[PDB]
Length: 381
Image (cartoon, rainbow, N blue to C red):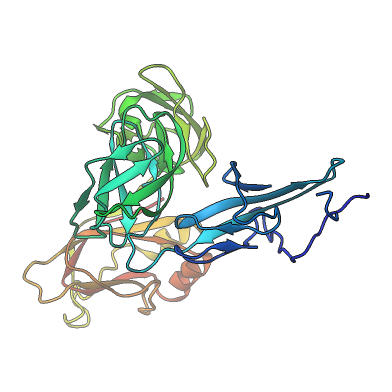
């Protein structure tokens, strides 16, 4: 007739600002882990203990990461609770699926996708009091995925999903966040004044206007559920606030390190052209040939550039060339980055360290070395 805290066994505690490691097992496996005057919870739900005792747990749940709570109360009212994580690893041959990056944020009435393994098997998907009849496995030049159409009736919220096969076996698919809100998920942190700015999110086809540094934009280059292109207003270099409102009138939300907000910090930068033209580069040319390298941006220019600036070299291929390789170097040909074998056009970007800037002055300036390509544009921001 007293007050307890640590009954056997020994449980580990949190290292950072994130929950305890705890149990890690398999899809088939079972979760097995004061006096007698002295409950189990999964993702915030009261559950039965496998056995008869309120200390001996036997639990076989579907694959995925879970939130376990061992909140035990005595006859009087002594308060000692344990909160931790329980990880259930699926079987190799089982239809696995985890989140790779933001595809789990889904919208009602719309398509969605799952990246994993064996999803070719998934005849149906289960999302909280619903059965998804049409799961289509789509074939890609990149990672393959399984497409599904989120039902209209589904209200907002976090849901655990199921992957049911032919027989009906039902396997472990992790967490899915459902939203109708116009939520900007990426590429808002940084923007360039007067150039196109392409922002990606979820219900962006409903964004009516976006406001950066007070300046409002209502006209958009492209607009759909996933993405939106606009022209970042003519703002001085600096950190601004971006807000936005829907066709309806609600505030456009902003996901950032999983923290949803109503305001976004945008870092506006201005892109200064250091050179334009169509300069071919071939190290096979003789020494002294203007086209052995690209070095038309004098040293004095590179001295000007402040540490952290972002150099971009717009390159274009020479179709007749047997190979296309390039590299950003000093005048002494010291590489500032790795060599690059490429086959199509593109833009090479490089943040310029104070060291890189020093090497530039120490070593005869900046060069664009390589074979079979054209330097078309060099810019800084």
